[PDB]
Image (cartoon, rainbow, N blue to C red):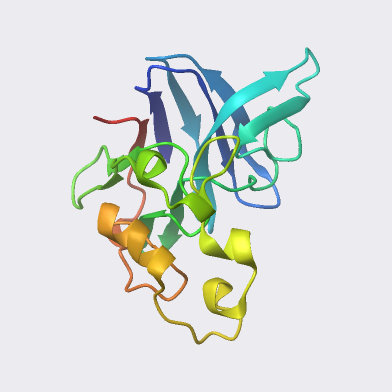
Length: 206
């Protein structure tokens, strides 16, 4: 499947793409404002994620640091990134279908649209000003708005037992972005698309 990753933000982002134990395609790249990066993701990929990283410094070896979404100090991510990270999540060719979503379970850093570029399903978006409105206890100094699990490390916020409810913090994310997951047991906002669809991820869509 092809994913076109577009930075419409006024600032540079460093895009990342991983399935947790491996890079997808090159795994990461700098995107200046307006740049597009096209990647190929192998059919059948389960548990893939794309995200943006902000305020990164990398040397000529591809080693450094980002203030949001850092993946072990590498330009080319092999592992998932450090919260806060707005997440585009996907599983492809799962019994004939593709499944896509946006999640705020690991917080929010950059606004995002995640849409098919082929026919047969709709896209999802979280484009509200979550960072500006972020509750004081969840604000990340590096930028972004952390989820409550990251901050407080409780069974309730992390849904450790598999029983948990919504919280004052999850409801904040949900009020601003109803079409994104706000906690682990949120009512699913996953979209089902035809198997082998292609997609576009747009940072700062509005």
